[PDB]
Length: 50
Length: 45
Image 1: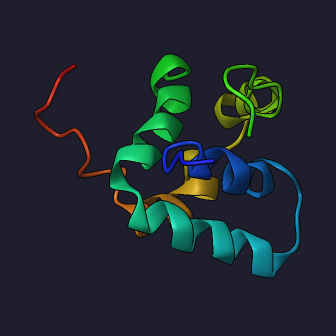
Image 2: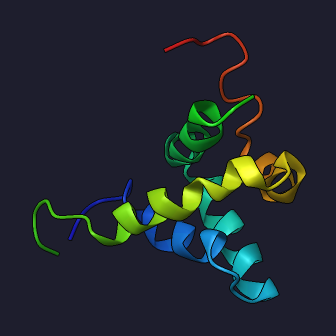
């Protein structure tokens, strides 16, 4: 109902899936407005870095 | 809507592993868009 953080999860769904080209560009637009959310994404590469 | 119970989000963590399989450049394009590169730098935590 009122969770700006989870907003990244919704969009992230398209960033992880082979969605269309337009979608990929959309998600990026959202994450851009959410600097505290994008931090979650890094968690992956951070926990999966070589 | 409902409190707790992610489900969807949990589904991402699964595919997230692909990140290690795919080149950082694949996401670097959008990454720089959000600014995940200069997110840490000298933060630590």
